[PDB]
Image (cartoon, coloured by chain):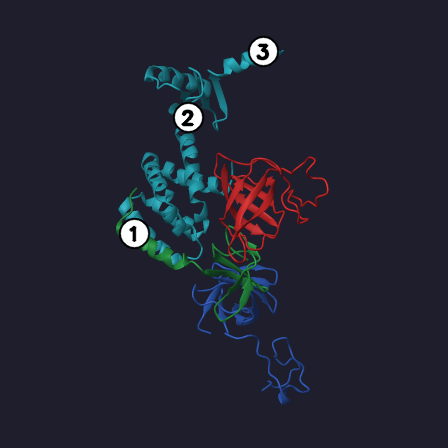
Chain colours: A cyan, B blue, C red, D green
Amino acid sequence: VDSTASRYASALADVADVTGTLEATNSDVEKLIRIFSEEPVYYFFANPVISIDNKRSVLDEIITTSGLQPHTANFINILIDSERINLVKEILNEFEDVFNKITGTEVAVVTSVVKLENDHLAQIAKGVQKITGAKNVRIKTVIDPSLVAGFTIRYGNEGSKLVDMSVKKQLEEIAAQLE
Amino acid sequence: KKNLGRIAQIIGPVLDVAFPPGKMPNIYNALIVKGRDTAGQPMNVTCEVQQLLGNNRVRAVAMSATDGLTRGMEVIDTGAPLSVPVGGATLGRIFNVLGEPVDNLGPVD
Amino acid sequence: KNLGRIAQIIGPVLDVAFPPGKMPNIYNALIVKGRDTAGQPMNVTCEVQQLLGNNRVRAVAMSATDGLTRGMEVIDTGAPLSVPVGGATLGRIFNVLGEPVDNLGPVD
Amino acid sequence: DEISKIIRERIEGYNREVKVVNTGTVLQVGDGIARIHGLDEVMAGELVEFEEGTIGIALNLESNNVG
């Protein structure tokens, strides 16, 4: 994807990569996402009517308490100057996808009714890695009542590529007979 | 004339002039741009504030040629629409859009 | 059971924003819980003509949109326009919506 | 990760002026049309009056602003 929100996030990651603050910058970006969740805080930055000069002063105070990275404080200042603070939320979310690309980590998300031990995951995370082509795999877990007793892992560029077996066997059987 | 704005765009005849945030010209005021000619001598090209655009910039249509104008030049707002000299001393003179006499005779009162 | 809020009113065209899960599909009617001039509730019926993405539909009002306000509650009715049919309908002048406009009371 | 009371209060102060309930601040004027940021409660066709006395009708209500 290449949209304005994605474009900005990619720049932010590239500067971190150059300066070797990828771990350090990522923590700050995660820290920002908590900040901009709040309807009141986001609204203040986003709306055109509040004066830009006031926004910087408030932003500076926020940065100090937060203790953000020197570029990360710039990056928000750049967004504010160039009017794209209305799409901060899209930009922050976009950065996580870019950050995995730079490392070579890949997310997978694996779904069960029942919580599973690391050993099963270790096989899956190794399994997604070879199948992925990954340098590294980072695993995301979710709990679902609806399937049966299996699970489905999703991976790829997006969460596009899903390979599952739990409910799906039942569905396949239902289809199979009608043939 | 105490308000200074910097040109932001020149697309043909239509300029966009960014002003300080409190003080912006009203619609139909004449902006007068501190532009320079091919000699380097300062030259003034008048503009009309056609519409307020938000983000503290106006959109003005220049009354003279915008060729030679640069993004970032000083634009002073005269605080009024185009005042044209009227009356007795305008009779038998030939005039500009701006009211400047165009017949190579001494300046209109 | 789905409640939405008008996002914008531009002429006879409304845009309604719904929560991310519950969401009308196209040609479902929407009922917009509006108010009247004197302030009593009167409701405008719409019909979804587009799905604009970001959980937002674009409905076209069947009544006048003068007086609708952004953020008023819109009850998704879950179906397209249900019109009374049957023996009862005969001899009655009907609206677009199935309301009687002939002054003989409700179609029972 | 956390917002100081001073920061929250400072942010809120700016918001209160702009979240004035009956009014809205002009975003751009031109060619006989004003765009207004705010006015969350206006209804379509409601007369709205600006400073210096001009009266206008809110024909277009959009999420970003009201024409």
10 Å neighbourhood of mark 1: few (<14), some, or many (≥20)?
some
C-alpha span from label 2 to label 3: 35 Å
The span from disc 1 to disc 3 (Cα, nearest Å) is 62 Å
**Mark 1 falls on what kind of element?**
helix
Q: Which residue is mark 3?
A: A176
Q: Position of residue D7 (x, y in %)?
A: 29, 51
Residue that protrudes farthest toward the bottom in the picture: B88
Question: What type is the residue that disc 3 sits on?
Answer: Ala
Tell me residue C81's x, y (percent): 62, 39
Amino acid type at mark 1 = Ile
Depth order, front residue of B107/A25: A25
Dividing the image into 4 quarters, which one contains the C terminus of chain B? bottom right
Residue corresponding to mark 2 = A106
Task: Tell me the tag on residue D7.
Answer: 1
Name which residue lies at 33% across and 57% down.
D13
Name the foreground residue: C93 vs A157.
C93
Q: Secondary structure at mark 3?
A: helix
